Amino acid sequence: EQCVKKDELCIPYYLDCCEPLECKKVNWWDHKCIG
Amino acid sequence: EQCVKKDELCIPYYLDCCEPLECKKVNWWDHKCIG
Amino acid sequence: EQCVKKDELCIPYYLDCCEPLECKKVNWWDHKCIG
Ligand code: NI
Ligand code: NI
Ligand code: NI
Ligand code: NI
Ligand code: NI
Image (cartoon, rainbow over all chains, first blue to last red; front, side):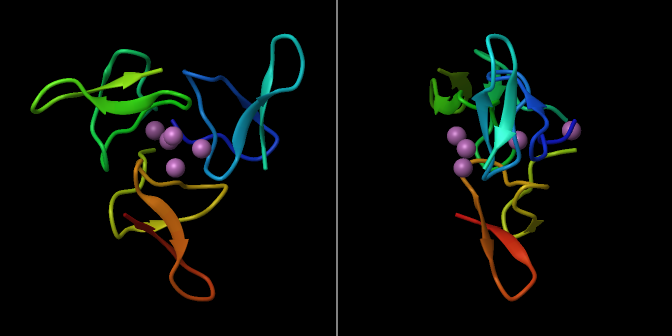
């Protein structure tokens, strides 16, 4: 598995972003890699 | 390889946790993903 | 894919280091995992 790229979906505690992106909520259920 | 999940074993500098978990020592030799 | 090990090449936003290493520029184009 790879670190998640910019603007792609991530899951805290399960599937995280490539640094320096941060996994941020974008709605009630989903998160995206932002930064 | 995947990021390490909650309460599973991690190794600093070698096998790290899924954010926002942190790899913490739990005894003399082992580390676990906590948070 | 795995997190990048100490003194190996990394790419911010694409191929990141094993914590607690940080991906730092080492010249105009390349980055390395330091820490
Ligand atoms: Ni990672
Ligand atoms: Ni981070
Ligand atoms: Ni961290
Ligand atoms: Ni992998
Ligand atoms: Ni970091």
